[PDB]
Image (spheres, coloured by chain):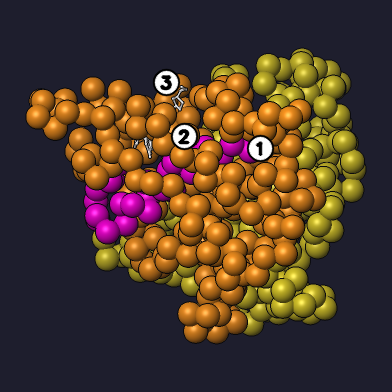
Chain colours: A orange, B yellow
Amino acid sequence: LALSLTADQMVSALLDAEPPILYSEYDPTRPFSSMMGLLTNLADRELVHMINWAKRVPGFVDLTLHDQVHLLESAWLEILMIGLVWRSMEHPGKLLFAPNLLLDRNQEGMVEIFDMLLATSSRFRMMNLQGEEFVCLKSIILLNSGVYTFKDHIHRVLDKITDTLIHLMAKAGLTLQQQHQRLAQLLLILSHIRHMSNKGMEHLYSVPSYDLLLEMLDAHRLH
Amino acid sequence: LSLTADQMVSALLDAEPPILYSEYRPFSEASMMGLLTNLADRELVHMINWAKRVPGFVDLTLHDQVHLLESAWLEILMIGLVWRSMEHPGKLLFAPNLLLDRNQGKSVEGMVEIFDMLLATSSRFRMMNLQGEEFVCLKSIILLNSGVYTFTLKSLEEKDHIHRVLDKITDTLIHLMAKAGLTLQQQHQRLAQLLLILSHIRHMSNKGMEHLYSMKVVPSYDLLLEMLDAHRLH
Ligand SMILES: CCCN1CC[C@@H](CCc2ccc([C@@H]3c4ccc(O)cc4CC4(CC4)N3C(=O)c3ccccc3)cc2)C1
Ligand SMILES: CCCN1CC[C@@H](CCc2ccc([C@@H]3c4ccc(O)cc4CC4(CC4)N3C(=O)c3ccccc3)cc2)C1
């Protein structure tokens, strides 16, 4: 039934599903120093809203809960990262983790990933990434990050998102050549977001459990 | 940059490296990694020659060429392996005389996880019926794209050039698919499917990089620079 939405209906649904921007849980009256504790706590709170968002991506909830959890397990860090890059676009050289937690690169192994995220924000700024495009990209990360590491339904939803992205670019006046060129440009940034998630995962080990994710998904009560 | 799509395909097909063999030290679990390392080392030399023939690559500085190869070489080995393996379900065709199944990939801690990811990519290629012309385009995208987000006025010019070459490879992939008779819808859908596989190949390369370091092991910047930094005396 979700595969029957029009491109405009798909965009509207994704825009409406957007999660809120959360704040860091630091007392702004106290001394600043604890950064990883604040960032970890923010990420933990941002996961619940991510799950609520995922449940509104058309087609996601037609999957079994087991497969929903596996997609979230694969995608959650990439999704946190692309959200961070999106909100940092208009803050050259800085990362807007929260509206009260804007850090620059001067604030072991952290700067390497900080620089990669700053480079993604700058690429988004160079391409003039639109909000409608960003929500489609985030939905593609959710469905594609865990699809090879477990499928037909996932691929049909991914195809619908590609159609929606192309529709947005055609509506913006791009030529057919510019549409395919921009689609490729946006999807190649996803490979860099995967790379960052991989390197970020290494840095953090230097993971939300299946049960935690399943609990956040709040299963229906008639099994 | 002025090549047509047809000329791009032709240049990429002509640049393709040869399929190398393993030595004919009999094969055993104990000798496996030595055999695979020796093969990869020989493939890397041909990979350098191939890269210099990818349109637009040698227009970049030496330093940037090295950086792009440093970031891409394992992905390139892997996608080559997945392509060689596409017609052999359940097996990885490292060489025509070195065709392994995943039970052979269990002797080393952490190998079977990567082996399975590679088999899954091979299966995906097969389900998509990936064409040879599409493959060489994807391999060229990996070369130009994997390191472009990890690099001055010269750097800005290099990045603009890389993105222009990437755009012409996109145009080439679309041309191939149009020529194959796909609708415009099917063309953008297949372009997206192909490019999303590159995210999985990046993931496999990062996991592979961790596995290689767990064992002992990469081409140094200086080694890659030595092979790329050729003289003109031959
Ligand atoms: C209860 C189960 C355990 N939990 C479950 C979930 C797990 C959470 C681990 C965790 C801890 C911290 C981050 C932040 C963070 C926070 C919010 C954001 O939106 C984005 C980010 C981006 C990010 C990922 C790179 N990050 C860093 O700090 C960082 C930024 C630049 C350079 C180096 C590091 C994300 C994720 C811990
Ligand atoms: C001083 C210079 C040092 N050299 C520089 C170059 C470096 C070479 C390290 C090196 C050693 C071995 C591989 C093989 C290999 C060989 C050929 C192929 O086409 C592809 C592959 C694929 C690959 C990377 C995953 N692999 C494995 O074994 C493997 C396969 C499945 C699961 C787990 C592991 C590649 C690369 C060492």
The image quadrant of residue B140 is bottom right
Q: Position of residue A145 (x, y in %)?
A: 61, 43
Disc 3: which residue: A206
Please determine whether, in this image, residue A191 is positioned above or below residue B117. below
Instruction: Please indicate whether residue B39 sits to the left or right of residue B221 in the image.
Output: right
State the predominant SS element of the stretch in magenta. helix
Region rendered in magenta:
A70-97
Query: Label 3 sits on what residue type?
Result: Ser
Mark identifier at residue A47: 2
Q: Position of residue A47 (x, y in %)?
A: 46, 34
Badge 2 density bin: few <14, some 14–19, many ≥20, Cα 10 Å: many
| Chain of residue at mark 3 | A
**Mark with earlier residue (3, 2):** 2
Q: Give the secondary structure at mark 2.
A: helix
Disc 1: which residue: A68
Q: Is mark 3 within 8 Å of ligand 1?
A: no
